[PDB]
Length: 276
Length: 9
Length: 100
Image (cartoon, rainbow over all chains, first blue to last red):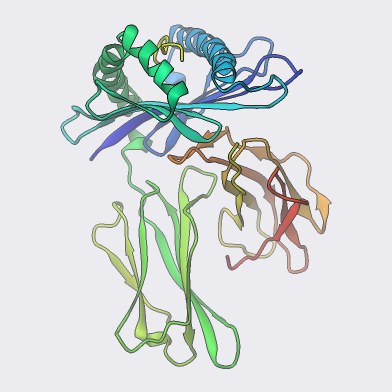
């Protein structure tokens, strides 16, 4: 199927406490594989997936140099943005950057993203044409003009379409045993009576990978649902994910409800009901 | 790998 | 300056069986700015040696973090997550419910 290489960079200024904090994380699909944190005397890019230890010192030295340089650029960018918005040096501000590429089933470039956010809001985005920009205000229009002056969109295309695609293929090969292994969800239904007249049916999906999943409570048209709840997909902590969906139904109608679970790791969708 | 030198804002 | 309050889930890595080693998780997501304080509590007392994941964020730029520690659930021990954020007037406490 499709695969993605994505980097997430955060820089947060610290008034009167030195240089901004800078944290970079890299993901292949839903698996984090690298991290850089500048809160160290000699900060290093480090592996966060064991299969990345197949990479030699040349790789880590190069990524460490890139991440250290990127942190400096973001410190400059925070100073520039503060001036664009006439903001004082006493406030903490956040600059975020997400970038990467998506491969199609053919292994070819499918889509790329390059997006900046300032204080939690879109700031400057490279459009899907990989040649025009979206600036959100007059400040971002200055940044857009500077990127156009420097032909940044063409340098982005070269990375997103070639460098990014080439290295995503390499990472997928180095970690194929885990990255390409689909782990289906383990599913069950639990029953929790609320009162004498109503009960909660909770449909569980545990230990699946990747994170994309659909949990749906279906009913036969004769069910009278009192309430529903679907929690955000959450990490189990071991590389897999969890999710559940609940419905509050009148006691005695439990058998009118069926939980439907769809996940790439299942050969076919699973249907569960509450059986004491 | 990371991209080198995002153009300054 | 945007502010988004954290969504909080407290849960275990594996279905809780009394007397068996497990992992207690506190997942905070959807928050902004990134500064946040998270502690795991056993019977109201702060658990030491609690680790957390590397700061990352979602498509809408909101941050997420996982805080976790090894634990062994019992019948009477109460576990909880205590979260402090700029959007919270006081630190919020969410008790662990083994069925959620």
